[PDB]
Image (spheres, coloured by chain):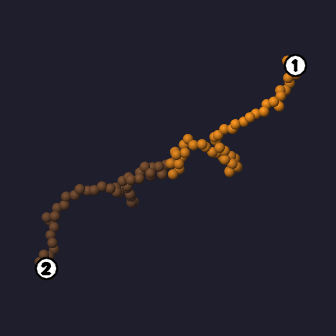
Chain colours: A orange, B brown
Amino acid sequence: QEGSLKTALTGAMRVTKDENDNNLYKLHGGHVSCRVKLSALTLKGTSYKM
Amino acid sequence: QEGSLKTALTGAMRVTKDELYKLHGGHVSCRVKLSALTLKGTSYKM
């Protein structure tokens, strides 16, 4: 029943696996919502000559 | 895809083999002639 399952599982969110890590499952889906703090970010060489 | 074919072929006329393919299904319309039959010994003693 490999074929019947695979045709039934077409278009389903996929999971893959790493190198040696054999219980580390990568989830091909979802997204992340982030808030980034920028005030402590500075330029270099603003007082360089042209 | 072996399972997928087998689900599709549930309720199919079946075939078998030996060593020739045997068709499991259908009937033979026969006409039987009986006038050439005889009883052995209608003149034995009871």
Query: Residue at 39% across / 60% down in the picture?
Result: B18
Query: Residue at 48% across / 51% down in the picture?
Result: B3
Indicate the quadrant containing the C terminus of chain A: top left, top right, bottom left or bottom right: top right
The picture places residue B14, in percent across and down from the top left corner, at 37, 55
Neighbour tally class for label 1: few under 14, some 14-19, many 20 plus, Cα within 10 Å: few
Q: Amino acid at mark 1?
A: Lys
Query: Residue at 44% across / 52% down in the picture?
Result: B6
Height in image: B25 above or below A41? Answer: below
- The residue carrying mark 2 is B44
Judge left or right: residue B28 versus residue B18: left
Picture quarter containing residue B33? Answer: bottom left
Disc 2 is placed on an element classified as loop
The chain letter under disc 2 is B
Q: Disc 1 vs disc 2: which is toward the camera? A: 1
Q: Amino acid at mark 2?
A: Tyr
The picture places residue B41, in percent across and down from the top left corner, at 14, 76
Picture quarter containing residue A11? Answer: top right
- The residue carrying mark 1 is A49
Height in image: A43 above or below B3? Answer: above
Query: Residue at 45% across / 49% down in the picture?
Result: B5
Check residue A3 in the rendering and tell me which mark sits there, or answer none: none
The chain letter under disc 1 is A
